[PDB]
Amino acid sequence: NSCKKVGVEELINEKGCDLMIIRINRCRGHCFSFTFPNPLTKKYSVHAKCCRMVEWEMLETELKCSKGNRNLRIPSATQCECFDCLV
Amino acid sequence: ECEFAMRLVPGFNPLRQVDANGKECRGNVELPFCKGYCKTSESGTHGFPPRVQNSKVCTLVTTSTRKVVLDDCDDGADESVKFVMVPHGTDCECSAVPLEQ
Image 1 (cartoon, rainbow over the protein chains, first blue to last red):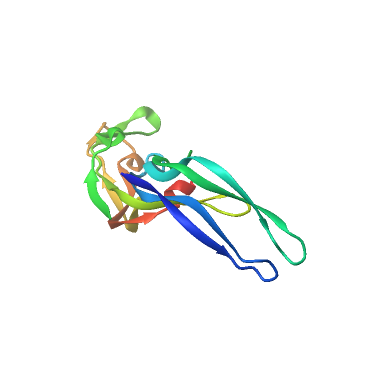
Image 2 (tube, one colour; image 1 turned 90 degrees about the vertical axis):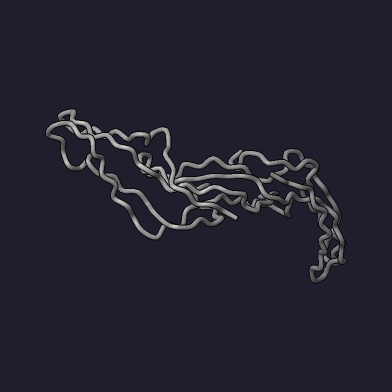
């Protein structure tokens, strides 16, 4: 189990607005999981971990467009961990 | 990345099936069992939904179906409870389909 925080530079290059570089965080990694076809329930019996961000921070900004500046919102990770995929 | 094995599950060690008239057939049933560490990720994104999940679990690659017979049967049991239909394959892959249902 290894779920790590990874920094991401992201370029916004939309026609009309000023380019803008945004530095955020995402979670990436490998967690354990197993699954078998339960025919008694006729469904998949799943017991799975997934690399997810437990806590995050919103990241707002102004995109300087020629026809009206916009306000953008992005989540950025603060703690990455192997947790339930469905929660 | 993933791993395949035929295993015995609590409910199927052994499996019991009861018909009308109360006649029961029991018997162990091996199940295809996929397990491993899939590469997963969660990232913040613009707009809605604000989050993106590359979530994946080790799932069986279904290539056929197996009809397993329960041996230990009560006298005069119906045939419908003497068999079980199980999806069967040979390899496991990282897939998100089990999470959907």
